Image (cartoon, rainbow, N blue to C red; front, side, top):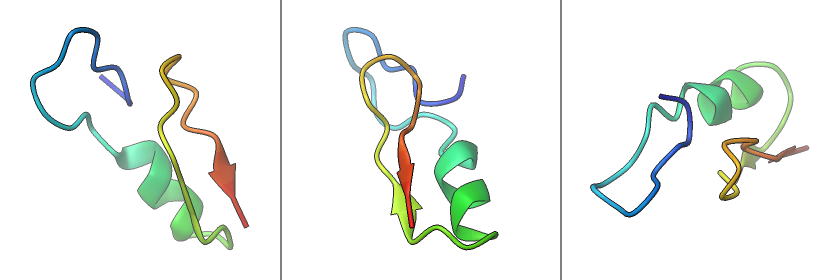
Length: 40
């Protein structure tokens, strides 16, 4: 869920990043703490 990857399998939900985009943020990279630090 979210941007959790753990060992590895592919890409997470990416909802967090998209959510940021659909607001004002340019995007957001999913850091390895499922924080998905977005950026304007």
